[PDB]
Length: 99
Length: 99
Ligand SMILES: CC(C)(C)OC(=O)N[C@@H](Cc1ccccc1)[C@H](O)CN[C@@H](Cc1ccccc1)C(=O)N[C@@H](CCC(=O)O)C(=O)N[C@@H](Cc1ccccc1)C(N)=O
Image 1: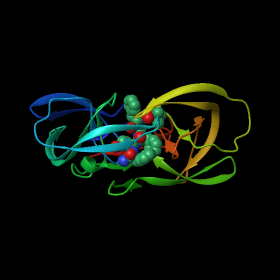
Image 2: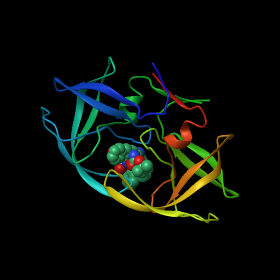
Image 3: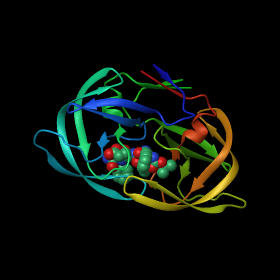
């Protein structure tokens, strides 16, 4: 699809059998989900944003469905206020900016 | 034009007589620029992202040129690590997400 930006580019995703809303973020290298019940092993990570920094949980090769389009890749889980879909997944589902 | 997301979607902006590089960010409601010589009156403000919050200086009705495209709007100035073009200005240049 095509999405205009008058509103947040919020979308439905499905991950670890659960349905969640998530923001399509071109300013994010990574995908960061709020605290959630995810299965598998992980590795400790530190990431940065406008406010400062937070510690995440690195989940690799995780399946996720974004607006009907499936992708596998790294998913970070931590103290973020919004679920964020970053370029590691945005490239996957073939998403582009247009103007 | 069309911008894929294999690399950060960085663009050349001109503002206040000066040339900078700014990141096209669909996850940002607002435009936030690093500290810069900007003329005029402004108003304190507090904003948040991953990591926490920063206080910015708010400039209303500032002209800015993005990849050739002229737009006028609010620009925020403060301790952001990088230049961010937000949805307030992204609408003004007809920018959309596509996938
Ligand atoms: C900037 C304002 C107007 C306050 O909006 C946001 O903060 N919007 C955020 C959405 C949000 C919604 C609700 C609540 C809080 C936040 C986006 O995530 C903003 N996108 C960029 C804004 C930005 C870019 C560059 C520098 C500072 C700030 C971002 O933080 N991108 C992060 C997303 C998190 C992530 O990718 O894991 C990023 O790529 N961070 C990199 C790059 C980096 C590294 C170290 C320091 C600074 C940046 C990283 N791997 O840490």
